[PDB]
Image (cartoon, rainbow over all chains, first blue to last red):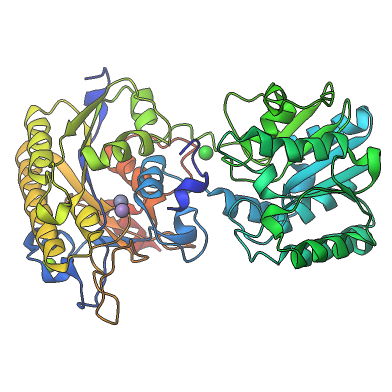
Length: 11
Length: 530
Ligand SMILES: [Cl-]
Ligand SMILES: [Mg+2]
Ligand SMILES: [Mn+2]
Ligand SMILES: [Zn+2]
């Protein structure tokens, strides 16, 4: 959630 | 309102259905089986089916879509490449050698004491890092001519099996000796110590003291695999490896050294990197002197509050649709119920908390029930009510909403509730459509990814996940026809450019998606002439 494309965007 | 509201050629209402994919298989398909007369008509004739998963939305191949990536890509009019995909492209296309921050770090070492360090999780886990990236960094650092390079190997055993580290170690030693003939392994320590994220600074200190002062077991290239095997025989696995120290003092992080962390996942890099590159070394409470004048680089941004340069800093994401409308002095309206409010704000606007000039927001409370299968219509009716009021007012040339039920009820895995969720959503869409025709808006309906079209696994069990199916893109304006891009399937990155084309507005250079409509007149000229 901290920047667009970080690891949370995988889910 | 905003000064240029009347410059638009067409006012657009964009509906983003959450979790509504296009699948012809009727088994467990709550959309097909639900009564959906409105979408049955909107998804006929001139409509499109666009991709919302995998590389089409910047995610690794084969990965289902989701609400965060989906609203991001719809809002941005470009593919935002997820870290893994982005870095892998850089490795494939030999772009590390010209990476601005990597060149910066190598220039610092070369203009300084010549000494550079690589530190991260060494395995093929791919959750926090990948060994392939570390190998690519070593080859680029060599080509860039850095005098001295040391590797600090963090043992995994969590994203890979607990005894695989010896293999990654063997791979690394051979890569350094035979493939590059350049670079030296300096430390091995388990991620339990190096990669804590719970403010257990006594664990960080074990890794810190290994790197700074060589506190650990002395070994060398010839002996280190055997040390690890002895650790394994004593039930000390990769995640928990106590420090092993190679190269002696020269391999420690010393005054004036430069250090790159290669993990791309920030959460477990924050502590060790702040210990090295800021003031959190105090928290380690070590008797060792902290080296002066270190510079720290991260593979990605670990915290905005850190001074560290990043090899792959965040996509700037300038001129997403919401920023671009404001720059064009066109006002806008974003509406969702509680469960998807972040998605129509933070995520749609580019993955940050920013509200642009002229942007009006509307939150509709989601129902207070234990689980949403108990009220499958959720608050779709309220969202439609708020959109209809904006259509009647005519204030905003671009309005958009989210409909939550298909996704949120889909996650309960209750098929009959999912059917009702889709029926209520279709009713709401119909009411918005009638209002757009009355009040002079063009309606476009899409989705952020699928879900409710697949409620059953093949064995008959519940399917509670998003999908890889395409999503619809509809358009009520009969002056345009859909046309696919030349070289790829259409995708969520094409929605915003298409909106702008219909609205008669310019497309910013930062939107590298393409409009996937064509005016009939222009298609007619292209036909009769080409
Ligand atoms: Cl960008
Ligand atoms: Mg149906
Ligand atoms: Mn979901
Ligand atoms: Zn979603």
